[PDB]
Amino acid sequence: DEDEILGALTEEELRTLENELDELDNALLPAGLRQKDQTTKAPTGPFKREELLDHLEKQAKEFKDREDLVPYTGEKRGKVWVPKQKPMDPVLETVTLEPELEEALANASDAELCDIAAILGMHTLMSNQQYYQALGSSSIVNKEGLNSVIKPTQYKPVPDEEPNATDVEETLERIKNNDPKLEEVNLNNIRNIPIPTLKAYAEALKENSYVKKFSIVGTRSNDPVAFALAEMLKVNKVLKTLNVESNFISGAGILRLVEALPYNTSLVELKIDNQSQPLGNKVEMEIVSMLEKNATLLKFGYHFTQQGPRLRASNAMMNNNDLVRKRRLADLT
Amino acid sequence: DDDIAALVVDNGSGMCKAGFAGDDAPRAVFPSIVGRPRHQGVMVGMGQKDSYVGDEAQSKRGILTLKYPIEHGIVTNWDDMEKIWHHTFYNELRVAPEEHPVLLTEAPLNPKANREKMTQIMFETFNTPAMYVAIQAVLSLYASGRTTGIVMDSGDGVTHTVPIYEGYALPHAILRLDLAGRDLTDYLMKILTERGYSFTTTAEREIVRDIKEKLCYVALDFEQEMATAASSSSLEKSYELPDGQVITIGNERFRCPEALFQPSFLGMESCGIHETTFNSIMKCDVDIRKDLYANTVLSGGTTMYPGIADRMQKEITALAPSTMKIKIIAPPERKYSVWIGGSILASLSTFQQMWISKQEYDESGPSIVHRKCF
Amino acid sequence: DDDIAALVVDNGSGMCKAGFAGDDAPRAVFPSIVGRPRHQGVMVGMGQKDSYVGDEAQSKRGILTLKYPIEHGIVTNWDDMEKIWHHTFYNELRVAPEEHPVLLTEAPLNPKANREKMTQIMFETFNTPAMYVAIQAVLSLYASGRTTGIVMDSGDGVTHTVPIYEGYALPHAILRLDLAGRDLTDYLMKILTERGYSFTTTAEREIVRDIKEKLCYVALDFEQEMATAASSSSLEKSYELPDGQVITIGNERFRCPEALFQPSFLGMESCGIHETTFNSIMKCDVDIRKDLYANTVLSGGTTMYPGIADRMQKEITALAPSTMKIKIIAPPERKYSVWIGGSILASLSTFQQMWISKQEYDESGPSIVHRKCF
Amino acid sequence: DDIAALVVDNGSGMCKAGFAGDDAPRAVFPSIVGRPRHQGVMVGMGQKDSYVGDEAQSKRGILTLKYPIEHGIVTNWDDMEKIWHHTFYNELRVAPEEHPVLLTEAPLNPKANREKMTQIMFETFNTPAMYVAIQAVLSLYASGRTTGIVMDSGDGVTHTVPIYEGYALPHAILRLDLAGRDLTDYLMKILTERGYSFTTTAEREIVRDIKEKLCYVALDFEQEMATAASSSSLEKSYELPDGQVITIGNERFRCPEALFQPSFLGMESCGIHETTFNSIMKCDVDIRKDLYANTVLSGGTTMYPGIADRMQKEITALAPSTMKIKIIAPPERKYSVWIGGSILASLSTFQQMWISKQEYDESGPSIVHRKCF
Amino acid sequence: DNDNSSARLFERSRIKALADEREVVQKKTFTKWVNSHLARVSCRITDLYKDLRDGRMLIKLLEVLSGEMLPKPTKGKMRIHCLENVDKALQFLKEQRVHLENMGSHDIVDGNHRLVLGLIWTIILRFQIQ
Amino acid sequence: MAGITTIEAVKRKIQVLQQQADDAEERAERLQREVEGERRAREQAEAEVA
Amino acid sequence: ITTIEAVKRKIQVLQQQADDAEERAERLQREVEGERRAREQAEAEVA
Ligand SMILES: Nc1ncnc2c1ncn2[C@@H]1O[C@H](COP(=O)(O)OP(=O)(O)O)[C@@H](O)[C@H]1O
Ligand SMILES: Nc1ncnc2c1ncn2[C@@H]1O[C@H](COP(=O)(O)OP(=O)(O)O)[C@@H](O)[C@H]1O
Ligand SMILES: Nc1ncnc2c1ncn2[C@@H]1O[C@H](COP(=O)(O)OP(=O)(O)O)[C@@H](O)[C@H]1O
């Protein structure tokens, strides 16, 4: 009875259903615009919080009290389970092997007791490391005891490393000046480097012929920095190693980086490990397929989730290193 | 004719629903909150019958402290459970628990004491004749009408993804991520405090939750959304407070749900929900992966963000192989669908074998739930 | 040139063990874990360094994400292997690898590119004059001291069984099963969830591995031990977390290694280690089986659980005919046996003919490893 | 006219069934029985305990798959009863009580196997008559020539028999246990070399499909190895059921080469060409000349592209120069063991060959040795 | 690969045609039989594969053939109720000594021609009109 | 059993251990006497049958 | 040099003596079975 079911619904609901079926949500509108606004009143005031608190308090005070039909008393109205008890095993036998050996083990401490407990085969009673050092040698080594609680390994403390002392503006100024005595630029783990500043570094290294290695590890770099570096790599002929590990570069940015590899023959090591999100297998397929195009790159640090692209990338690295070996051999003879 | 069937009680982390089996909609919907007088003994012990429950608790937000008895899907306080359950049985449903079987839901990988304690409360306090415990994700797959697919369920305490192929569950591929809407509420407060609106207590918690429900959306592109929000103010909206003051959210509308996809904002070392679904699919066999790609089902109240489905489809298609197709089923009624699953599952004629009757409980105790259920 | 002593390096999935040839024990034992910065914030303790290698990474778990370069005996990350090898050569043995030969180990059934890439990396980045690649389970039999028997090795990445009769290995009877300590650790996390405790991150993985190495044992009879553990709390033991709280594992201490004997707990349809060893014996000829029953040799760090020897003997005695005599040889130093036999192998006078020269590599490329090694 | 008998071919890999006098079988399905692995949480679903035939192959992920026949010997008989029930009642929709049944057997096998089949088919299915025939005799029937040597190769057993003018030589019958399943396992073990991992029973079907699509027999082995090592023009790409793409390459022709060199599997037996030559050489001097020109291939395993040229070249190398070698490989040889059977039940004198119900009732299940060859 | 092509060629043609013609005439006969037996009640089957999918037709056919009462079919439009309706008829067949192989409720629900034809043939052969 | 002592259980195990060692000793002497008797009987039978 | 180390040494020596004792016993048992197996047929042949 479709007509009766529709008549059971409200007529205003029927008109709303017709309007909603005509609207079908808002798929055409973007994600932000598809929501309706709450009220039409303009924003006013610097949000005085105490007025909110006082209004809420008096609103709570002048409220009519709902009275519940049945009060709660915590009454248990069902049968208690009362778990069963067992008669268990009431056995008692004395072994009494030797008056000598009675008194020998009667006054032994628990730490030395656990050695003879473990040598007889109660492996369940104590920990495994304790159990094995008990069986290690013919002497009492066990200090802890079977009853005592086990504790984790502490390993060894590591001394604190000095924080990064490489300043930003002077380094960029020296890079822009083509300084002959600046070869390594380190930017690892520096607080709050501006994105336009990193881009300024990216165009600054375009014309620098004296810096051989670069690193922006842990700089919270993003896709525009990746795009600018990808643009820079085509021009530059001196940079040996680029390190962009531990960043927020998306898959498309990494694709832009690998797409610059055929144009330049000066980069030998590139590391893109530990990114915030996985790149996806399509990006991996593109990376490996057109990294097979390049013949200069030797070291590439990336953990491939799939097996096919990983195998092909390993083969490509093997081929590049074997080309180096072959040209050395041909140069010798 | 079995005493108008059983009762379906979907006790979610932040809000509880209850109703009769065989009905499409739950009869009672109310938050799972216990409100107590805060610190004072003023006005002749004002705040009498100190436990305020449900709608009456949120009515007196100013003069009370609101406590959630369920945190992360685990019962911290059991007296508050049995108070809430008494309120459901007597104050709203107005039916006796002695003649009606009860169906209950729980998270997949929960500590084992919860099932035994729920069985003890059902059989010792409300003396129900029969009871069963199920999983919300299986109920969601029941509500979707399909017998093959992967189910995400994200409530206020827990997110879990399970795969099911042809009615056979794969226990090794079930995942549990502890990133839910409460964390999004806290992150929304954190980013609102930077703008200038500081929200601290439980009344502020309810207000911020209402703001999040009414004004949030999942951006398709995060950096494009940042550029748009910095360039112009068209994305900005206005929210009025109960007293009358009006504030502007603006940049905070899409940053709140983005922590679902990037947990680095929340301060958690975890992967996104899309990575959880993809890893749950990779943990299955080779052949049944394709169907799990074509039957992704969303559920829970958290998935009512606008544009979550298209964004997560884009992410999955970024991860998945390009040969096969990806589709996402996002019913508009999914927030209640878990309960609807119970309304299906208690309605089946073959389920009458699966009830845990009182006679077996009186011989086995609360441990029988480990053998009878799942 | 008797002063030139070769270096014996075993690259296990969990730990790397390096030492000088002709010694009874390895000089350096350290886990192969690479730690990298988290994304929640900047670290406190390191500046220009990009990553931490070895026990330095293990100590600073709270600010690092830990990655294993070896996955199931396969080198997924070759740069991570270069970092591990550099740390081994320069920070633990404190010797220049240019002046010493290097001996390495390998799992039996591997991708063929593993040996080639290993040889190329060693020769190009370390300039060693000679090197060699050997297979682990032959070195185990060298360490045991006999030339006839079956070796069942179980490391941190893979399990493999191989028979040897009078020094002739049978390649058609070698079996490789993917069951090691990492899957046991993951199952231990999954079975520690229902007691209440939760472990998610990689530091939690190391904590769970430390719990497993000290608390787990193999039950002789599974049903009898299950009934005993349900009967009373005699088997329960306590552990101290680094935070300060004390946990009590109880029942699941002997449930973790039971996956080695029933893989269906992990969802895989493979057989246990006892069935694998029996199948490997049945693949050989009829005549030599009588020797192979008498000389079963255990190895690997995974077989360090107490009670494994009697259980394996009982299972094989159930499988094998009644006439035959079975004994299991479990050396007390077996955890380092793969290294120890290597120290034997570099000491033999014939083995000096078997090295791979720098010149031979120079003409023949990295493909010389297939012709020169087994 | 009389009722047409049912021709049922029980192979190690596939089971075929049809009516006598037809030119093709009417039902072909794999001889696989699968059972559920995981647990079922959905209530109200199907409660079937065993998947059989194509239905088991339809759902591989949640099943452990088993073969009731291995190496030409039945190991599980309940699964065989399920196979035959699904063949009769579902695939053909016939009543077995009114149809004679013809069955197919390898030449050398355990004797009791025969009795069991007879003891099943007269008891559970109540057939009025039944008969058992050797595979290679039916293959020679379907070849159309009375004189020849038949080499057959399936998933369980390889066998060569010589027949001269309808007379068989029992002492020259040769059997070898290298067959298709061994090639599948060797392909798995050799695909491990490239890093690809296949372990479960469901993945063995994937490996079998890869072998059927992308394997061929090289005419010269060392030259092919040199060619495959020098260039990458021999590689092919396959798509996994989950969208992964793999590359076989050098493993395409190394797997079938194991048929000619059994030392790859550790077996010390000789190749198939050596087995055929030895079976010819065991015969009398006079009948060898007709046997050299009438070699017949049969079975699915002989469907590798290039097997005929390699077999002819090797046999010509072994044979004396003045004799000429002809390898007869019909294009539909995969069903030859069926087709000749469909011929054999249509003959006039074969109505005098049937093992009747009364004869079995009189002389028990051991009657099959007196009637069947 | 001309011989492999010819083998696939023969496989694609002769086996498929010889099975298809038998299947067509068998289903045409079975439709007539089930329509003659279902005509006593106000029911008719116009398609063998589609009308037996839902399950009411099968349970009514077992009702009229057995002459003996069957439990209430569950009411509902989803797949699960359909699985229930097929499963109850399968259980009723399981009681009265009829032996079935490769029969699941989801096989009839999904619509496999071989299994529904085999089920109808088994009903004709082994079940008793009585 | 809730009430137990480690010393007592260890002591019972020592008892069982010495019982095992003693049993194996009667086993050895048992079987040595048996094999000598059987060898002598076989030799005598062989001589007289020859 | 005390009594407890002597206890550990004593029980360890006893244990390995016991193990060697069952090894020798079972080997001797199988040899005994073979000898009796041979002798009985000789008696039957005498008859
Ligand atoms: N209209 C809405 N838009 C966006 N989010 C919503 C909406 N309604 C509810 N939510 C979110 O859903 C959550 C409630 O989930 P709920 O279904 O109660 O979880 P449970 O499974 O524990 O019942 C709230 O925290 C809120 O953030
Ligand atoms: N005392 C112990 N008891 C039980 N298991 C252990 C113990 N020590 C190490 N293990 C297990 O052995 C593994 C290390 O094995 P290892 O010898 O490194 O394997 P590999 O052969 O790869 O070197 C660890 O992951 C741990 O799970
Ligand atoms: N087109 C093909 N090319 C190569 N090998 C094939 C082909 N088709 C089938 N095979 C092999 O033949 C086997 C099937 O043989 P089959 O005729 O079913 O044996 P039987 O029926 O005697 O058991 C399969 O295992 C497969 O390995």
Image (spheres, coloured by chain):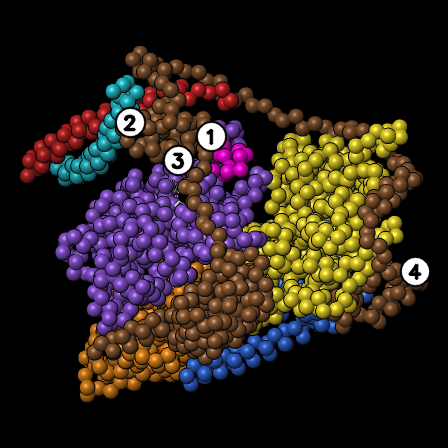
Chain colours: A brown, B yellow, C purple, D orange, E blue, F red, G cyan
- When the figure is inspected, residue D219 is found, relative to residue B326, above or below; the finding is below
**Left or right for D29, reference E52:** left
Q: Name the quadrant of the C terminus of chain C.
A: bottom left
Q: Position of residue A66 (x, y in %)?
A: 90, 38
Real-space Cα distance between discs 4 and 1? Answer: 69 Å
Which portion, as a residue range, is magenta?
Answer: C237-253
Chain ID at mark 4:
A
Check chain identity for marks 2 and 4: say if they share one. Answer: yes
Q: CA distance from mark 2 to mark 4?
A: 90 Å
Other-residue count near label 2 (Cα within 10 Å), few / some / many at <14 / 14–19 / ≥20: some
Q: Is mark 3 within 8 Å of ligand 2?
A: yes
Real-space CA distance between mark 2 and mark 1, rounded to the nearest whole angstrom: 23 Å
Query: Can you identify the residue that label 2 sits on?
Result: A139
Whichever of labels 3 and 2 marks the residue nearer the N terminus, that label is 3
Q: Dot 3 corresponds to which residue?
A: A128
Apparent side of residue B273 relative to residue C352 in the rendered image (left or right): right
Location of residue C331 by image quarter: top left
Question: Residue C281 got which mark?
Answer: none
Tag 3, which secondary structure?
helix
